[PDB]
Image (spheres, rainbow, N blue to C red):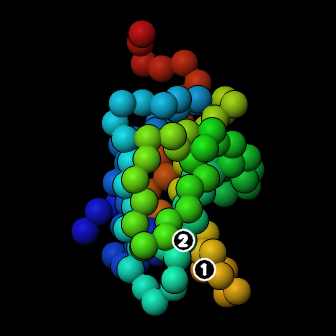
Amino acid sequence: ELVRTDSPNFLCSVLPTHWRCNKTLPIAFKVVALGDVPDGTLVTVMAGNDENYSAELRNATAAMKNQVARFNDLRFVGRSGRGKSFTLTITVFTNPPQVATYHRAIKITVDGPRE
């Protein structure tokens, strides 16, 4: 497995985002989504609080084609956030929109423990 979504059939590789305005970190990113679709899917990273749905990202909206993606552009809690958890979701790119959510969302810091 990998950072899977609803099922181990759609797999991600990212590093934690437990703070506001993630930026283009040197960590880079990958996704692999196994199915019969001609494309792969669309991954969107959304920070809310079960009742907030604020979402806010900086290119953390990313599509897949040969059922794979390669990038470093994706940005979580983009134009800032506070008091929210990171609801990473895979939103599918065909007639039946297949919307899948990531196991563990972890609440984000404004400032930090110390800097």
Query: What number is the disc on residue 49?
Result: none
Q: Residue at x 58, y 24 (%)?
A: 110
Q: Nearer the viewer, residue 17 or 28?
A: 28
Three-letter code for the amino acid on which mark 1 is drawn: Gln
Q: Secondary structure at mark 1?
A: loop
Query: What number is the disc on residue 98?
Result: 1
Residue 14 placement, left or right of 57? left
Q: Look at the picture and state if 105 lies above or below 8.
A: above
Residue 65 placement, left or right of 98? left
Q: Nearer the viewer, residue 113 or 56?
A: 56
Residue 6 percent coordinates (x, y): 46, 75
10 Å crowding of disc 1: few (<14), some (14-19), many (20+): few
CA separation in Å, label 1 and label 2: 9 Å
Residue 33 percent coordinates (x, y): 41, 73
Q: Is residue 103 visible?
A: no
Three-letter code for the amino acid on which mark 2 is drawn: Thr
Q: Nearer the viewer, residue 82 or 55?
A: 55
Residue placed furthest toward the top: 115
Quarter of the picture holding the N terminus: bottom left
Residue 67 percent coordinates (x, y): 42, 73
10 Å crowding of disc 2: few (<14), some (14-19), many (20+): many
Q: Residue at x 34, y 36 (%)?
A: 27
Q: Look at the picture and state if 80 lies above or below 102.
A: above
Please report contact status of discs 1 and 2: CB closer than 8 Å, yes or no: yes
Q: Is residue 77 visible?
A: yes
Q: Quadrant of residue 42?
A: bottom right
**Can you identify the residue that label 2 sits on?**
41
Instruction: Indicate which label's residue lies in the foreground, 1 or 2.
Output: 2
